Image (cartoon, rainbow over all chains, first blue to last red; front, side, top):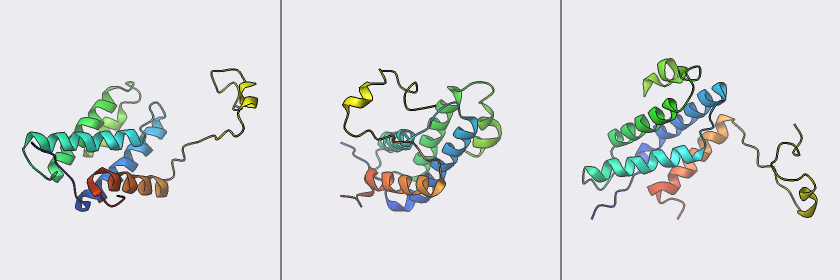
Length: 92
Length: 49
């Protein structure tokens, strides 16, 4: 029954997050985070909205999706590459 | 490295194809922000449709 959507009001932050993910990733250089990761953030945000029976995706759902994506990407890295967790992506 | 030895298959296979596009990824942020905005417009932005 639940087919959620987003709205342009939540574009800004997501774009910036994508950029940050990219730049800490090439500095590391170990794992490419491409447009596929942005589109996985979007999908997990839709799922987060779905579990709340909401019809629009709130910014907190986007924050949770970003957290899940960055945690999965970080935990798939090396210990040497894992710095992005402590001081790069600690904001998310 | 050259496009050959950077690829799995035989080098001369590049002769068979008429045009070969090397789609390199540019990490410039202007492009990153534009691509993210476009891809969000795709995802429930409904602007592109």
